Amino acid sequence: CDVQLYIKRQSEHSILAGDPFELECPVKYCANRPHVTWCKLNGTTCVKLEDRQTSWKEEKNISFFILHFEPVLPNDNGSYRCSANFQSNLIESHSTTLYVTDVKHHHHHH
Amino acid sequence: PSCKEDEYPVGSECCPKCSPGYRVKEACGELTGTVCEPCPPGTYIAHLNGLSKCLQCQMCDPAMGLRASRNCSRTENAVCGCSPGHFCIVQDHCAACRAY
Ligand SMILES: *[C@@H]1O[C@H](CO)[C@@H](O[C@@H]2O[C@H](CO)[C@@H](O)[C@H](O)[C@H]2NC(C)=O)[C@H](O)[C@H]1NC(C)=O
Ligand code: NI
């Protein structure tokens, strides 16, 4: 089989700071599961993530490498990418863009 | 055309650039990501890139009184400086040194 990452071009999500949320990077493989990581884009560099962290959920013919936001903070705004090392090669996914609304400082007047 | 800092143009749409130390082997689609490939020995790329071939490593010929102040790696170019007891006589950086 061919390894590949299935994030759609211009993927975006709109979520509330304060709620929990997961991003799911769909990974295709068959033989050995590849080492996957997530990173947030800050311009030129994609800085890797490790503090509030990741996990796998495996489905029939496609698995999901999951970045957990527990809860989502206001500063979690921005673009995110997963990368997969398989047999020395590297697959760079389309980024997905989180638009977090700061519920604390957001007010309905009505 | 309108690609973000981390994306590059292929066809009429944008695409994820490869990491430093890697070149583009196969281009993205609408749903699929960009396949990247390690730079061969003696080549490098220093930044996020959509290059299908890596750049050549700078050489530091000892016959020109040059020692490598830093080696070439896949992610970094080699930078030539002068060898023990030598001073620069040709300039971006030094390309030749004479002895004292
Ligand atoms: C660049 O790499 C060369 C080769 O790996 C280094 O030169 C070696 O230095 C080590 C000591 O650390 C010795 O074991 C070898 O005999 C040296 N090899 C040769 C042919 O010179 C060099 O020091 C490195 N320079 C830097 C700063 O990265
Ligand atoms: Ni509202």
Image (cartoon, coloured by chain):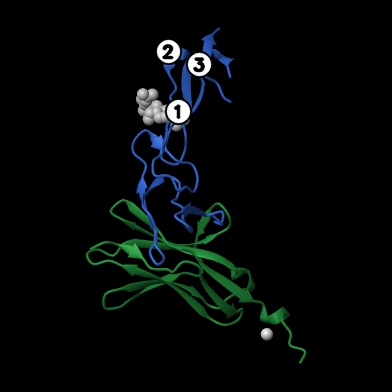
Q: Amino acid at mark 3?
A: Pro
Q: Residue at x 57, y 82 (%)?
A: A19
Residue annotated with mark 2: B63
Labels 3, 2: front one: 2
Quarter of the rendered image showing ligand 2: bottom right
Residue B23 location in percent, x, y?
Answer: 39, 46
Query: First in sequence: mark 3 or mark 2?
Result: 2
Residue B39 appears in the picture as rendered: yes
Residue annotated with mark 3: B84
Query: First in sequence: mark 1 or mark 3?
Result: 1
Assign a secondary structure to mark 1: loop
Q: Chain of mark 1?
A: B
Residue B62 location in percent, x, y?
Answer: 43, 16
Mark 3 neighbour class, 10 Å CA radius: few under 14, some 14 to 19, many 20 or more:
few
The quarter of the picture where the C terminus of chain A appears is bottom right
Query: First in sequence: mark 2 or mark 1?
Result: 1
Residue A47 location in percent, x, y?
Answer: 52, 57
Look at the image and give the colour of chain A: green
Q: Which chain is blue?
A: B
Instruction: Residue lying at the far right in this picture: please name it.
Output: A109
- Disc number for residue A53: none
